[PDB]
Amino acid sequence: TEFLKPRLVDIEQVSSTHAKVTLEPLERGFGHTLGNALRRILLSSMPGCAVTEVEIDGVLHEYSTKEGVQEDILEILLNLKGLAVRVQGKDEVILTLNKSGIGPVTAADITHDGDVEIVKPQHVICHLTDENASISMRIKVQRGRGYVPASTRIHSEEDERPIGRLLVDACYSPVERIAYNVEAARVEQRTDLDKLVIEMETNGTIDPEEAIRRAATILAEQLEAFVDLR
Amino acid sequence: GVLKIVKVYLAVKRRIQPGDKMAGRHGNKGVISKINPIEDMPYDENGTPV
Image (tube, rainbow over all chains, first blue to last red; front, side, top):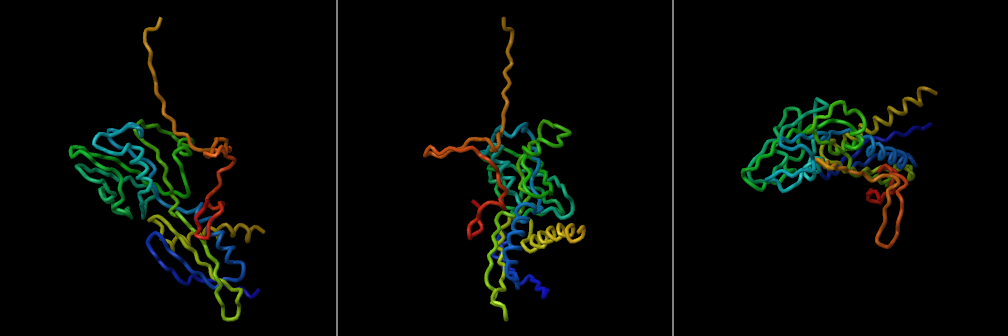
């Protein structure tokens, strides 16, 4: 075995959302081996934070309509699914949003909690039409992984049923898109030696660099079981 | 005979799922057999899954 390890070379960060990562040198065939294995974990297994429960005062269910608000509660909730959140310390944080008057309610109207970071403060949530109208809600953000729909969550625990809580989808998975390209790394001697270019596209939260590190960690954790137990 | 009547209205959100019937506009029907994870689905050179 003349073992030949790759090392992380170039991190083009085109945007906070989109980031390209070249990787070399790779031995022949390891391009696709690592490329797909990482793609699968990055789509299905990636950990993140997302809105789980929302409680608006003066709102019993998600199908009602609040006066002075253009959007029905369902449409407001769908906007909160797209709310990009980082929790630093705790696993579960409840943010408060109180706003009034005429204007597009943005994510910045949420009371900035110390550890919590809102990635997109200009994110639209609600449009207030009448000046007398005020909206007040308590948005719970939990940390998990993958996709946890409200329907899969309405058939598990449900120890308490407080008439007033609304369950909405929360895509924990930060990763929106991922593709890997195997290009030739015309290596000093070897022409079969190749590079792996991983084009990642996330929403907020996870850093591209950090996410790749985590995904490789999960794969290596799973291999400990096979290298160890025979 | 009837003294009073109470009408309850229930609301239900139904998710798409295996067994559900889907069609196009050219009379092309089908039943959904399986929901595939994003990772598994055929993807473009650009990486976008079908």
